[PDB]
Length: 117
Length: 119
Ligand SMILES: [Cu+2]
Ligand SMILES: [Cu+2]
Image 1: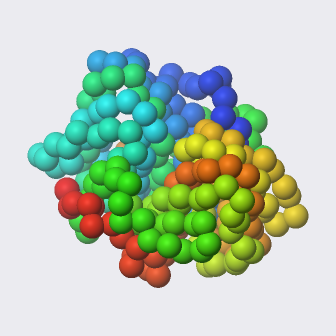
Image 2 (image 1 turned 180 degrees about the vertical axis):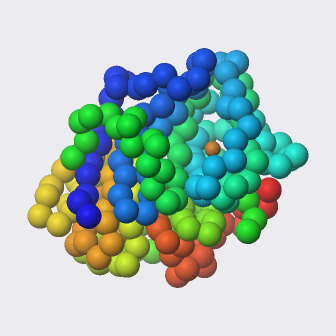
C-alpha cells in the first residue's frame, strides 16, 4: 500500500543463471518489476509460471520464443506473455530487459535492490 | 488469451496532452503497457485512477510527484504508484517513459499501435 522509487544503479544485481543477472526494481499489490542483465550467448530456459509477463528490451538483441514461434527482439521492442504459457529466450548480444509480472511474483521480492523508496 | 509482440516504431504515437504522445505497446489479461513521448517543458497533470502504475524512464529527465513525495527521475530509474494515489510529473528534458498498468486499463487500448502482432 506504499509507493516506492528506485534509482538506476549497476550494483545489487544478483546472479540467477549463467550470464543472467536479476534485480527487482519496484513492486506493489498487483505488479512486480525486475531488470535482467544478460550477457552475449546466454539464454533463459523454458518455464511456465502462474504470472503474466510483459517486458521491454532496453538494449541488446535477443530471440523470444513463445510456444513454437520465434521473434527477434531489439531495442524498443516489447512483449506480453500470458499466464502458464511456455516461453524461453536466447540472448544474442549483451542485453538489458525490464520485465513486469502480474500478480506480485513474491518469489522475486528477495531480489530487491535493498535501496528503493 | 493471446500473447503479443510490438516492434519499435517512431510512428503510431497519438497526441494525449500538449507535448505528450502516448502509444499502447502490448496488453494482456492483467496488465497493459504504454510508451509516453514527452517534450521538454510539458507535464502530466495530477490524476487518481483505479490502476496500479509501475514505470521505467528510458531517457530524459523528469520530476515525479507521488502523494506528498517529490523525486527527480533520470534514465534507468523506476517507480510504482498504487491505486487511487495522487501523482503528477513535470518534464524537464525530452524524455521517454514506459508505463505498465494493472489491471488492464481498457481505456488505453484505443492507443494501440498498428505494429503489434500476436504470438
Ligand atoms: Cu518467465
Ligand atoms: Cu497515472
